[PDB]
Image: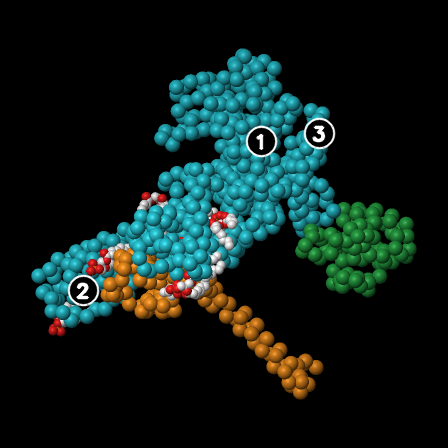
Chain colours: A cyan, B orange, C green
């Protein structure tokens, strides 16, 4: 369990003993066998350090490049690089999981990663090690993208090896240096329409736990790729969707405004042009409601977000789904001869208009207002509700109790006190209650405590949030644009087929196996003239 | 911010007018009353006995909390940011404005340019 | 169009080859002629780097002062400083 498979070779490794590892692997110890334990497993419930399961993986993670280079080439018992553990981390994946974005750690892990890839290329030209998906089903590229490791991902995105024998693994090819512009040719390997965990998907679909999601899309290839996707086809599809939604909301508003007032539903169709227009508008409205219901169900089934992180990452989808629910309840009440249907429909009307702020996320300068509204409704107001309600209820019950012998009921007292809290009430002291002085004291304390002291506290916190997320306009709207691009591409399969997302699918080299490979790529010209 | 506010105003105005068709009589007056709410200048009464009174109260309270407490203060925070940003750079701003007015004054009256003696010698 | 007027003298320039420019301008290449292309023009719709049109302008913009000093004084074919391109940038303007 704890000490399952661990031997003196690991202890020599972690202590940096050059000769002990050589002696042990000369003795014939089977480095294929893996050591696992509670301390090794990535469990928060127990203390431990994760270094994979393969002993070669531990040697690599523990900063020993010559030692692992010998282990691999040790004729007595070479270690297999392609070993995949039950936990689901390969040696390369183990290195990815070790990294913590630090500059020195970035340099260390990148150097050892490049060295180990070169060694593997020397070892097994026939096999490509990178693409083998690990136990969880995501390759080291996808794992680095999803986990948050910007340092490990940046190099892999612009992984260029100047050795002419390693050109079949380099990701970035420098086409020429005609000037400060340096033409590029990335591999776009499994970035778009590839597999379960594409790089863009894991970057964007992530549950926001990752700590540097915004900075990931600043890498050299991702920015150009997303901008190309936006300009090519996505932009006009989004604008068409916005226009169709505006028409839908206008039709819904016109249909609901001119609803019949005499009788109970359903309402018999009368022979008039206006009646035909009204009924067709109602049919279109209900059709849109059904569409949004099904799109919400499809989204929730696809992503299946966790209950805790449901609202944080799916605010707009939640709101569209709730609007669809309201309209469906309205139609259900319509055919049950209940006049209450209207009361539901208006909630789907008022809501339907405000949901249009979703589309402001498709513009740069106007896109932050939706973000601010979402954050100020989920973070500040939500948890200030609890702080306010103890005050409201305490003083409401106290006032009602004091004068039992507009403040007659508990509902009206709560409403009047809430009006006081927003500076919208009248202090009169006109009626001759019992204990008038105590009533005046209670109301003045409430007004000073909630109107002057708590309301302004809430406003200060809201201003802090607005201030904080108003600096980061570029990052915020870039991420929102990326998410909408992903959703637009994924919604219409024919759209993905006709996207021409990649620049081209050309074979720009010959593999050491002897067969030239056709790889996807796109141009990325970057200007750097100061460095000459 | 006009665009962000008008969706709220129109959505809740149309909703309120639709809800009680059977001061909130017309669409113009409903829009005006809701705008007055947005600037803390309206009266919550709930005195007339409408249909669906609870839903009407819920709609108005949501509107007041969303626009008077949440959007208006957002606008005020952004305005304060702008004021703060262009209140540090007093010297540069007024220097540029003085330069522009000098140019326009010199260019307006040709005799003024002739008699300017702009150059030292 | 793209490769209109560009010759090996420019390629020696941008790579910082001291001797290649001397050889080319000893060969009698007419440095009066200007090279223009889509990459050279200051167009946002296309990628490119602007360095004027005159080859001397490119030599100057590409950080080569002794080389241009010789081009100007090269008795075989001195470059004219006062050359004005159709785009509208002089060497100084470049
Ligand atoms: C008709 C073509 C409908 C497809 C377009 C589409 O899905 O747009 C959609 C509206 O479209 C509708 O739902 C209205 C449907 C009726 C419109 C008829 C009026 C025309 C006169 C546009 O919206 P969307 O991008 O589907 O979703 C945005 C919000 N979620 C659902 C992604 C969270
Ligand atoms: C895209 C274009 C969308 C723009 C659409 C509509 C905007 C234009 C409305 C002008 C109508 C005036 C006539 C009038 O009031 O008489 C009505 C006939 O009019 C109707 O019933 C037509 C309403 C159906 C609209 C659905 C469009 C979907 C088509 C795709 C009958 O009487 P009434 O006046 O309803 O009764 C009093 C009602 N109030 C005044 C108390 C409210
Ligand atoms: C007025 C506010 C109206 C609705 C807000 C409800 C959503 C609040 C929580 C969303 C994010 C979240 O899960 O926070 C995490 C969970 O925190 C909570 O459990 C808060 C629950 C409050 C519910 C009301 C942190
Ligand atoms: C600062 C607050 C100043 C307000 C003090 C007086 C309030 C109005 C008032 O005096 O009410 C009149 C008299 O009531 C009183 O005497 C009550 C005095 C209590 C005042 C102390 C409140 C302090 C609480 C702050 C926290 C109404 O009855 P009448 O006019 O005597 O007939
Ligand atoms: C915090 C807000 C506290 C206000 C709650 C009660 C509002 C006034 C009220 O109760 O109206 C009276 C009763 O109306 C109701 O029962 C409606 C209750 C809905 C209150 C929930 C509002 C929450 C919305 C916030 C977003 C008027 O009719 P009556 O006096 O029964 O004859
Ligand atoms: C998150 C949820 C469920 C929510 C659903 C409704 C009831 C909502 O009240 C809240 C709670 C609330 C109530 C009153 C004041 C503030 C907040 O906030 C929103 C929700 C809060 C909004 C605010 O409008 C928006 O957020 C638009 C919007 C912003 C950003 C988006 O990404 C977006 O995509 C859809 C939409 C308006 C209402 O949806 C609306 O139109 C009505 C009548 C009630 C508002 O519950």
| Side of A316 where C63 appears, left or right | right
Q: Are marks 2 and 3 on the same chain?
A: yes
The label on residue A113 is 1
Q: How far separated are the C-alphas under marks 2 and 3?
A: 86 Å
Quick one: A93 or A116, which is closer to the camera?
A: A93
Label 3 secondary element:
loop
Label 2 CB less than 8 angstroms from ligand 5: no
- Ligand 5 shows up in which quadrant of the image? bottom left
Tag 3 or tag 2, which sits nearer the N-term? 2
Residue at the (48%, 29%) spot, across then down: A136
Residue highlighted by disc 3: A516
Q: Position of residue A468 (x, y in %)?
A: 43, 54
Residue plotted at (91% across, 55% down)? C76
Whether residue B38 is visible here, answered yes or no, is no
Of the pair B88 and A165, the residue shown nearer to us: A165
Label 1 CB-ligand 3 distance < 8 A:
no
Q: What is the secondary structure assignment of the residue under circle 1?
A: helix
Residue on which the image places disc 2:
A406
Residue for point 65% across, 37% down: A520
Q: Badge 2: how crowded within 10 Å, few (<14), some, or many (20+)?
A: few
The answer to whether residue A134 is seen in the rendering is yes
Where residue A343 appears, as percent x and y from the top left, is 32, 55
> Which quarter of the figure has residue B40?
bottom left
- In the picture, the quarter occupied by the C terminus of chain C is bottom right
Marks 2 and 1 on same chain:
yes
User: Where is residue A423, by image quadrant?
Assistant: bottom left
Measured from the top left, where is residue A360 in percent x and y?
49, 55
Question: In this rendering, is residue A428 above or below A116?
Answer: below
Which numbered circle lies on residue B18? none
Residue A424 image offset from top left, x and y in percent: 28, 66
Residue at (37% x, 54% y) in the render = A268
């Amino acid at each position: 369990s704890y000490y399952k498979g661990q031997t003196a070779l690991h202890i020599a490794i972690e202590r940096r003993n050059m000769t002990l590892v050589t002696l042990l692997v000369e003795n014939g110890a089977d480095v294929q066998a893996a050591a696992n334990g509670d301390f090794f497993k990535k469990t928060k419930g127990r203390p431990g350090f994760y270094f994979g399961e393969l002993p070669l993986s531990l040697a690599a993670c523990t900063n020993q490049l010559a030692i692992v280079k010998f282990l691999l080439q040790n004729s007595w018992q070479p270690a297999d690089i392609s070993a995949r553990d039950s936990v689901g981390n390969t040696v390369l994946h183990a290195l990815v999981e070790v990294a913590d974005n630090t500059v020195d750690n970035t340099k260390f892990v990148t150097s050892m990663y490049n060295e180990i890839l070169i060694l593997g290329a020397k070892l097994h030209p026939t096999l490509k090690l990178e693409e083998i998906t690990n136990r969880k089903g995501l390759t080291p590229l996808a794992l680095a993208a999803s986990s948050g490791k910007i340092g490990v991902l940046a190099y892999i995105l612009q992984r260029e090896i100047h050795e002419p024998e390693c050109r079949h693994l380099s990701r970035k090819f420098t086409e020429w240096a005609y000037g400060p512009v340096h033409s590029s040719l990335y591999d776009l390997s499994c970035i778009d329409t590839c597999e379960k965990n594409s790089v863009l998907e894991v970057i964007a679909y992530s549950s926001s736990e990752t700590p540097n999601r915004h900075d990931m899309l600043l890498v050299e290839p991702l920015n150009r790729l997303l901008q190309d996707k936006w300009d090519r086809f996505v932009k006009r599809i989004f604008y068409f969707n916005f226009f169709v939604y505006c028409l839908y909301m206008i039709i819904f508003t016109a249909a609901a405004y001119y609803r019949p007032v005499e009788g109970l539903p359903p309402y018999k169709l009368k022979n008039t042009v206006g009646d035909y227009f009204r009924v067709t508008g109602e049919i279109l409205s209900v059709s849109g409601g059904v569409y949004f219901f099904f799109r919400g169900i499809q989204y929730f089934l696809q992503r299946r977000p966790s209950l805790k992180s449901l609202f944080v990452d799916s605010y707009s989808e939640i709101l569209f789904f709730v609007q669809s629910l309201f309209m469906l309840v309205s139609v259900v009440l319509y055919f049950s001869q209940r006049k209450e249907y209207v009361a539901s429909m208006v909630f789907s009307l008022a809501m339907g208009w405000t949901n249009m702020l979703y589309y402001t996320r498709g513009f740069q300068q106007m896109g932050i207002y939706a973000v601010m509204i979402e954050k100020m409704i989920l973070r500040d107001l939500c948890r200030f509700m609890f702080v306010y309600l103890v005050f409201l209820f305490g003083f409401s019950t106290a006032v009602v109790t004091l004068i039992e012998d507009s403040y007659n009921s508990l509902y009206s007292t709560c409403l009047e006190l809430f009006k006081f809290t927003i500076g919208m009430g009248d202090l009169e002291f006109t009626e001759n209650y019992d204990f008038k002085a105590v009533f005046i004291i209670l109301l003045l304390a409430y007004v000073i405590l909630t109107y002057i002291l708590l309301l302004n506290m809430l406003i200060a916190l809201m201003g802090e949030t607005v201030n904080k997320i108003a600096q980061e306009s570029k990052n915020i709207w870039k991420l929102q644009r990326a998410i909408t691009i992903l959703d637009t591409e994924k919604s219409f399969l024919k759209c993905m087929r006709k996207a021409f997302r990649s620049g081209k699918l050309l074979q720009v080299g010959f593999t050491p196996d002897g067969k030239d490979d056709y790889r996807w790529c796109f141009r990325v010209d970057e200007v750097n003239w100061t460095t000459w």
